[PDB]
Image 1 (cartoon, rainbow over the protein chains, first blue to last red):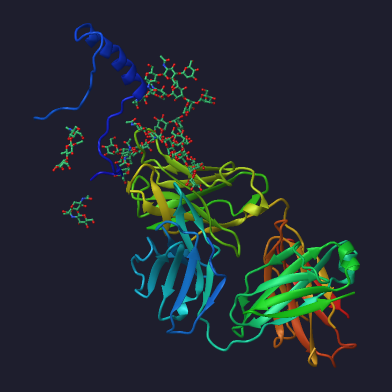
Image 2 (cartoon, protein in one colour):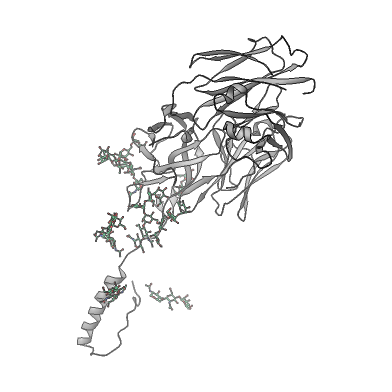
Length: 48
Length: 204
Length: 230
Ligand SMILES: *[C@@H]1O[C@H](CO)[C@@H](O[C@@H]2O[C@H](CO)[C@@H](O[C@@H]3O[C@H](CO[C@H]4O[C@H](CO[C@H]5O[C@H](CO)[C@@H](O)[C@H](O)[C@@H]5O[C@H]5O[C@H](CO)[C@@H](O)[C@H](O)[C@@H]5O)[C@@H](O)[C@H](O[C@H]5O[C@H](CO)[C@@H](O)[C@H](O)[C@@H]5O)[C@@H]4O)[C@@H](O)[C@H](O[C@H]4O[C@H](CO)[C@@H](O)[C@H](O)[C@@H]4O[C@H]4O[C@H](CO)[C@@H](O)[C@H](O)[C@@H]4O[C@H]4O[C@H](CO)[C@@H](O)[C@H](O)[C@@H]4O)[C@@H]3O)[C@H](O)[C@H]2NC(C)=O)[C@H](O)[C@H]1NC(C)=O
Ligand SMILES: *[C@@H]1O[C@H](CO)[C@@H](O[C@@H]2O[C@H](CO)[C@@H](O[C@@H]3O[C@H](CO[C@H]4O[C@H](CO[C@H]5O[C@H](CO)[C@@H](O)[C@H](O)[C@@H]5O)[C@@H](O)[C@H](O[C@H]5O[C@H](CO)[C@@H](O)[C@H](O)[C@@H]5O)[C@@H]4O)[C@@H](O)[C@H](O[C@H]4O[C@H](CO)[C@@H](O)[C@H](O)[C@@H]4O[C@H]4O[C@H](CO)[C@@H](O)[C@H](O)[C@@H]4O[C@H]4O[C@H](CO)[C@@H](O)[C@H](O)[C@@H]4O)[C@@H]3O)[C@H](O)[C@H]2NC(C)=O)[C@H](O)[C@H]1NC(C)=O
Ligand SMILES: *[C@@H]1O[C@H](CO)[C@@H](O[C@@H]2O[C@H](CO)[C@@H](O[C@@H]3O[C@H](CO)[C@@H](O)[C@H](O[C@H]4O[C@H](CO)[C@@H](O)[C@H](O)[C@@H]4O[C@H]4O[C@H](CO)[C@@H](O)[C@H](O)[C@@H]4O)[C@@H]3O)[C@H](O)[C@H]2NC(C)=O)[C@H](O)[C@H]1NC(C)=O
Ligand SMILES: *[C@@H]1O[C@H](CO)[C@@H](O[C@@H]2O[C@H](CO)[C@@H](O[C@@H]3O[C@H](CO)[C@@H](O)[C@H](O)[C@@H]3O)[C@H](O)[C@H]2NC(C)=O)[C@H](O)[C@H]1NC(C)=O
Ligand SMILES: *[C@@H]1O[C@H](CO)[C@@H](O[C@@H]2O[C@H](CO)[C@@H](O[C@@H]3O[C@H](CO)[C@@H](O)[C@H](O)[C@@H]3O)[C@H](O)[C@H]2NC(C)=O)[C@H](O)[C@H]1NC(C)=O
Ligand SMILES: *[C@@H]1O[C@H](CO)[C@@H](O[C@@H]2O[C@H](CO)[C@@H](O)[C@H](O)[C@H]2NC(C)=O)[C@H](O)[C@H]1NC(C)=O
């Protein structure tokens, strides 16, 4: 039996640190896909 | 939590005592016999514990919580406190409700008020004692007044106790300075029993 | 399951009050309930003190709850191997005089959300009375109460500040039984005790025939008789 918080497992990511990284990464993709373009992120499509 | 001061009923009748200030369902009621330890008669509102008769039932409507005892008997005579969790983890208790299932018959109290003595004032002390006895039920509130305005200071009141004749008795002690005693002529002592009050007054 | 309180029944003011509960039939290690204390001042309502539990979470080594007012002056402790509960009160005053009960707290303790939520005391102890006094054993001050109804008036003997109990007051050394009464003791704000007595006698007896009460106090070594005149 589970004795404690009734919860589902969870993963924490700091909003500031991920964003800062994202901004630096998204600029690197534009060294290929061109200086100006729209880059959108989305979760997994589907599968196993 | 606000709990009614007193409650009375005859054997076989059903009494419902309330409690307010409970916004949550953590409400619980306790039963404490005089000269004994408190015992939990109910928890989580309606739910009953082990070895507790069905006639005890908890109920909560809105901000008001209520306990109901049907089929009164001798062993039900005690003080009933309510309590509940509030906020994060703190818990508070009410003033408690005193329920008495004593035998008949009802009777008006009897008050005898004694002013300070001559030897006592010489010790630079002044104390007035109200003696209340022969009343039913066994719960009485006492009030003091100096002339007309009431006295809020120096009031010591204790829980009444049963006598040999089965009638309850209590005594309230008012301790003050001899200066305010000689200044104010008359000192009134008000004793409130089941709505009706009995008053006594003494002057030097 | 039995809770046995133990410790000093008499403590001096401003000192440190220490009390220890001995549990029997259950383990303090059990995560099903919290362990703490609830004090009930004489002829007054129930007041919550506090409770704790070693059964912790990922960010703490345990949980400890204090009553906001009593927080500064108290310390709670649990001995898991020895199955004992501790309570320590610093700088104690006569206002802290109460019957202390060893309390087991039930509620959302075994399955909670966020913090644990204890809400009710399922199991109580017998409890002990701790009286806080800044003084020592005291003799009662005896003053007579002069009467004035209904053909028979009432007179009594006043018993002022004393400590500790008891005091036995008899009228004319047990000469009168019928129509004799004695009221219980009262706790003063100074930590002391006080009580009185009353007797009903006819008005025709007033005269050369007088009434004298016999006061007896063992601890302060006090035997005092006083005659009463109106
Ligand atoms: C992923 O990210 C997640 C974030 O997105 C992250 O979640 C965060 O997790 C951390 C921990 O992992 C959380 O931090 C903890 O939070 C606990 C709960 O905090 C809430 O409650 C307190 C208390 O509020 C009551 O008391 C105060 C003061 O009286 C009142 O002002 C309140 O109104 C309220 O009062 C009610 O209740 C009283 C008691 O029942 C009643 O008396 C009263 O009448 C009222 O009914 C609040 O202070 C908190 O507010 C703070 O946060 C909000 C957020 O919006 C702010 O807006 C706000 O300004 C505040 O900053 C909040 O509401 C904390 O208790 C806990 O801190 C305790 O533990 C640390 C351990 O080191 C101690 O150092 C610390 O001193 C605290 O100890 C006390 O409490 C513990 C129990 O928690 C006791 O065991 C201990 O003995 C001590 O108790 C003593 O003090 C008590 C008062 O505090 C007293 O009641 C006791 O009797 C006793 O004397 C810690 O900070 C954080 O909240 C999460 N955040 C979120 C958003 O989820 C997640 O973890 C991440 N995942 C991973 C894997 O990392
Ligand atoms: C998740 O849930 C679990 C429960 O499922 C929680 O686990 C509990 O956590 C608490 C808190 O740590 C534990 O209490 C500790 O107990 C140990 C001793 O544990 C042994 O004995 C226990 C009792 O056994 C007896 O009873 C049982 C039941 O009746 C009976 O069957 C048995 O025969 C015996 O009669 C056992 O239960 C326990 O078993 C556990 O561990 C086994 C592995 O060892 C495991 O197989 C079992 O399944 C079970 O899980 C074990 O045999 C105490 O020593 C300890 O006290 C120290 O630690 C706490 C913090 O943990 C601290 O607050 C204390 O102050 C104290 O720390 C001082 O002393 C240490 C030495 O004793 C010292 O090293 C420290 O540095 C510190 O010393 C300093 O400070 C003090 C003042 O504080 C000072 O005086 C010193 O001089 C010095 O300066 C704990 O009290 C529970 O045992 C444990 N399990 C259960 C079932 O409750 C868990 O907390 C939850 N949360 C998380 C995040 O996991
Ligand atoms: C994943 O988890 C990790 C680990 O928990 C997270 O990384 C930790 O992040 C926290 C907060 O972001 C950080 O905690 C602070 O660390 C400081 C040192 O680096 C401490 O000084 C500070 O303590 C003060 O604040 C606490 C809370 O307010 C108080 O409880 C504490 O007593 C401190 O207060 C003192 O100091 C002040 C002056 O500043 C003084 O006035 C007071 O009197 C008192 O002395 C915080 O605890 C940890 O350091 C981080 N750990 C690491 C290893 O980096 C990470 O953020 C998590 N990620 C996600 C996404 O959730
Ligand atoms: C996403 O990344 C951006 C940067 O591209 C972050 O913006 C940052 O916002 C904080 C305020 O929340 C700025 O801090 C500020 O600093 C100034 C100067 O010291 C001060 O005057 C302000 O009071 C405040 O403290 C920070 O400077 C700024 N970043 C940059 C590079 O300027 C943003 O915070 C990130 N996302 C989130 C979660 O906020
Ligand atoms: C990644 O994020 C997307 C966006 O939320 C998730 O897609 C969501 O998938 C659920 C199915 O599990 C969709 O529910 C469906 O709704 C439609 C419209 O009501 C209905 O016709 C279906 O029968 C079903 O109920 C949900 O709508 C959809 N989100 C959006 C915005 O359309 C996806 O699940 C996420 N991936 C993972 C792995 O979590
Ligand atoms: C999961 O289900 C089992 C029963 O299959 C639970 O075990 C019972 O728990 C109750 C307590 O309410 C006991 O009275 C029974 O004797 C237990 N039976 C058995 C066979 O162990 C179990 O509690 C459930 N999960 C938990 C531990 O919460």
